[PDB]
Length: 317
Image (cartoon, rainbow, N blue to C red; front, side):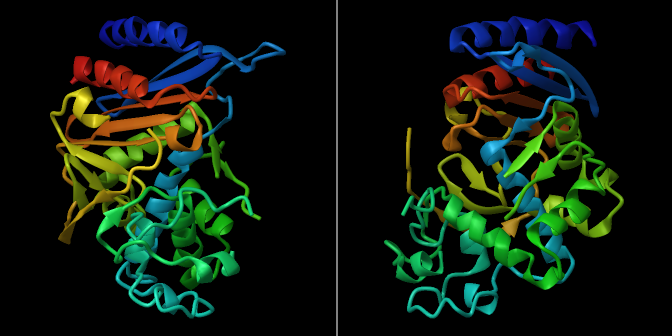
């Protein structure tokens, strides 16, 4: 690796691993469209199996980006529109509320207060669930929302969510060691590097609908403060300071972006695994052809991920 990448990575990540007591981590820095790999500590922490470029990590909430891109791909295939009501794809949902709730609302956590997790205690739950606010006014980060989006998004495909993901996203992007097991995602630093490159430069992707799908996942649908909501991905205008980038449930009023702004290449585009309890983090700046994946098992505080990522990307940019 270039000395600059070498320097910034070790100068940044080692202090992170020791301050947070992280047992194992893999990092990929993509610089000018090329990945450079780094590993520390253990996958099997107890039995001391070292992290390698092929170590599988559970992505946790970073999984949502794959759902966002599969959704985008389905839009590009003419299969769904985000303005379609939820009841077009799940008619069993015969409630006062669900009319007026669109796929857009599900994909972007703006349905009106669907919960972060499906309660420990589905068709029963969803029918009974009533919205705290009108659809499309407040963003509340929710698995029960984007998880429902994904199940409905693949109804026109003639494939299970698992098959659609594998054949429309994993295979075309040659993500050979990436798995979903659906009755989310585990992957390797090599595959995640490739995932970052694909989202950094959709124009090198030859599958036409996927290229458009990746691009649609970075459209700006809602704005709250300095952040813009994509499909899975979240974005901020670049340059930004780490402080502006960054402790449970936050339901936030959003401004509708009508029509959604096409992917702005001058963006800090990112997703954290942190709100699910997973140590993964991805960020990239399309216009700089620059990105980073940080995979870990230990769920360390999210502000530390951003600081480290920003350190590295700011140095290289």
